[PDB]
Image (cartoon, coloured by chain):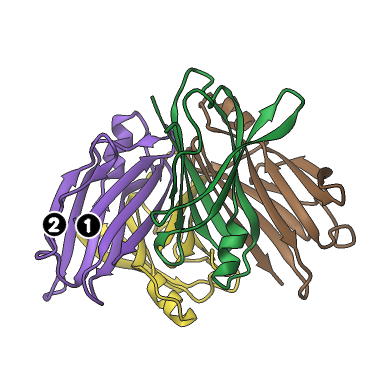
Chain colours: A yellow, B purple, C green, D brown
Amino acid sequence: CPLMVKVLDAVRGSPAINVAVHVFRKAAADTWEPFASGKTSESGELHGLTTEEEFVEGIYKVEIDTKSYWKALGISPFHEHAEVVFTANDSGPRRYTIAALLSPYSYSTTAVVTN
Amino acid sequence: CPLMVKVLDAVRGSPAINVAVHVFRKAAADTWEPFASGKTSESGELHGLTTEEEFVEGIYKVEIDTKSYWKALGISPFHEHAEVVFTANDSGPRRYTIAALLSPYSYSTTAVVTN
Amino acid sequence: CPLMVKVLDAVRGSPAINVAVHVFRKAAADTWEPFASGKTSESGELHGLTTEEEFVEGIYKVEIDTKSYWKALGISPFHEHAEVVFTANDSGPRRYTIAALLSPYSYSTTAVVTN
Amino acid sequence: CPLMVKVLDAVRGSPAINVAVHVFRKAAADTWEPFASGKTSESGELHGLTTEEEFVEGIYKVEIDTKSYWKALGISPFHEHAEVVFTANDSGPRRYTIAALLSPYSYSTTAVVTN
């Protein structure tokens, strides 16, 4: 699993469940091509987005559909979504965990990159 | 001053100075149109991006060029930029402060919205 | 104004108003001595806690009463308070801004230190 | 495992390894009594601090020794430690994960409380 996404809810103190996540890869024509997507599990995690073979170096974007999550909870949010844009770089074996902590008017995101 | 951006550096405990910021507005053709740009000051703030007249209702994207900021400080960071996407002025004009707190592998963003 | 505290609410996207703040200084007998206190203003800021003369080198604790803030808004939060503990003025006088961003089950704190 | 602690490093994008963590329970004399402690693992986690039998309702404090972690890395930090203070409440079965994200001049903490 070279790429996983973990989302937490800072209002409820819980995993953020059933959040849609879309991953895009930047293409030569400077456009964003859909790459993978899914919904977070009961643990707020999304595994199995890609494989080591497919996840080559390049620029990627992870869009987390935060507005629809807060709307389901009946809480007015600020952002349309949270966008995490980064370059995947081969420098020995790597696993990328994109973590996001959500509040209605704020989010934080971190990358945990391990061997 | 209906739109202000404030950027802080969590490594040095200081304003993040000379950070480039680009603002876009979503146009009718589902494309991002350039709206305003600038660089943060010695206080880590960017004022004067727009006026109440020009800042109509719409979906806006504030792109903070964090990668160039870290690289100039000798750090190879994770993110290409911090992107903040939101609907503005949909219930009438508001004043928006978009704050971002930067670390090499993490950032947080917050909005302070006043009437 | 060598010590200022700023508190924001990540649920409402607003300053956190009327938040009680207590500052303590560690004394020679390994105890916390009361140093200053106050409440945040309409801008979520608390100024005038101390003077350059009184704010000597030492270990200080800034306790932000977040539980009372959330309870007054109808939320039963996780934390009793947000505690910020730090050594001040050990390399000469500095100006400190202690910022806190609050959510019911999370908070972040940052320091902006200037010469 | 009713209480675990997870610590991440926002400068390196990694788990924060070998961080000392001390847990205290508030006693009737309004003093903090040592309850449990340990060091985070290679995954930045600390498990096995307490048991369901011992972890009764009360006020607890989790101290994360952030200053010594940054000193080991040769980076000047702001805080002496990060302190997370909360009330444990029995309202059906609960597991508490205290997560902390560290930067030299900032930290965020979240509680993930699950059944």
- The answer to which of B115 and B103 lies nearer the viewer is B115
Identify the amino acid type marked 1.
Leu
Upstream in the sequence, badge 2 or badge 1? 1
Residue pictured at 49% horizontal, 36% vertical: D105
**Quick one: label 2, few (<14), some, or many (20+) residues within 10 Å?**
some
Residue A39 in picture, x, y percent from top left = 47, 74
| Above or below for B89 versus B2 | below
The residue singled out by tag 2 in the image is: B50
Q: Which mark is residue B3?
A: 1
Q: Are marks 2 and 1 on the same chain?
A: yes
Residue C17 in picture, x, y percent from top left = 46, 58
- The answer to which of B112 and D56 lies nearer the viewer is B112
Please give the count of numbered marks on the rendered protein.
2
How far is mark 2 from mark 1, CA to CA? 7 Å
Which quarter of the image is occupied by the C terminus of chain C? top left
- The answer to which of D24 and C83 lies nearer the viewer is C83
The answer to whether marks 2 and 1 mark residues whose Cβ atoms lie closer than 8 Å is: yes
Q: Which mark is residue A50?
A: none
Residue D85 in picture, x, y percent from top left = 69, 52
What chain does badge 2 belong to? B
Question: Can residue C70 be seen at all in this image of the molecule?
Answer: yes
Residue pictured at 64% horizontal, 62% vertical: C78
Question: Can residue A14 be seen at all in this image of the molecule?
Answer: no
Q: Residue furthest right?
A: D53
Identify the amino acid type marked 2.
Thr
What chain does badge 1 belong to? B
Position of C8 with respect to D90 (left or right) is left
